[PDB]
Amino acid sequence: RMKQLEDKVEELLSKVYHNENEVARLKKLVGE
Amino acid sequence: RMKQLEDKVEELLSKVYHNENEVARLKKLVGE
Amino acid sequence: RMKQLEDKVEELLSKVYHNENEVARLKKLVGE
Ligand SMILES: [Cl-]
Ligand SMILES: [Cl-]
Ligand SMILES: [Cl-]
Ligand SMILES: [Cl-]
């Protein structure tokens, strides 16, 4: 379970960062 | 702590996916 | 590895919530 967990956190890290970047751009495009 | 961790990753998975979906729609609505 | 994992989930919790809040506002600003 520890390796399952670490693999999944590694994946979540990436998706969260991606979402941060997309939100940053959207904020710019809307002026927020 | 292992069960706490897994429960929390399970919850984070869901929220991240939800955020991905909402961002996808917003990108469409703004044209991004 | 357990402490590394918990520290990282704690950080991901925060970033996910932040992203939720930003998405909520954007949805309002676009009308989504
Ligand atoms: Cl990171
Ligand atoms: Cl997220
Ligand atoms: Cl998933
Ligand atoms: Cl939380």
Image (cartoon, coloured by chain):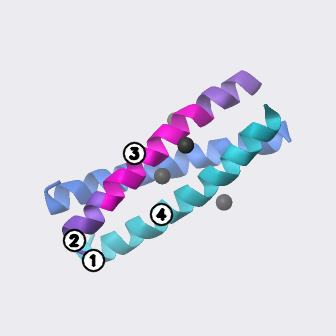
Chain colours: A cyan, B purple, C blue
Q: Label 3 CB, ligand 2: below 8 Å?
A: no
The Cα–Cα distance between marks 3 and 2, rounded to whole angstroms, is 18 Å
The Cα–Cα distance between marks 3 and 1, rounded to whole angstroms, is 21 Å
Marks 2 and 1 in Cβ contact (< 8 Å): yes
Residue A7 or residue A32, whichever sits in front: A7
Q: Which residue is depicted at the point 81% across and 35% down?
A: A2
Q: Which residue is depicted at the point 60% across and 60% down?
A: A14
Callout 1 crowding tier (Cα within 10 Å): few <14, some 14–19, many ≥20: few
Q: Which residue is depicted at the point 39% across and 65% down?
A: A23
The Cα–Cα distance between marks 4 and 1, rounded to whole angstroms, is 14 Å
Callout 3 crowding tier (Cα within 10 Å): few <14, some 14–19, many ≥20: few
x, y (%) of residue B14? 47, 38
Circle 3 sits in a helix, a strand or a loop, which is it? helix
Labelled disc at residue A29: 1
Labelled disc at residue B18: 3
Left or right: A3, with A24 as reference point: right
Q: What amino acid is at disc 2?
A: Val
The Cα–Cα distance between marks 2 and 1, rounded to whole angstroms, is 7 Å
Left or right: A14, with B14 as reference point: right
| Residue on which disc 2 sits | B30
The Cα–Cα distance between marks 4 and 3, rounded to whole angstroms, is 14 Å
Q: What amino acid is at disc 3?
A: His
Query: Where is B32 relative to C24, above or below?
Result: below
Q: Quadrant of the C terminus of chain B?
A: bottom left
| Residue on which disc 4 sits | A20
Chain bearing tag 2 is B
Span shown in magenta = B9-24
Circle 1 sits in a helix, a strand or a loop, which is it? helix
State yes or no: residue B16 in magenta. Answer: yes
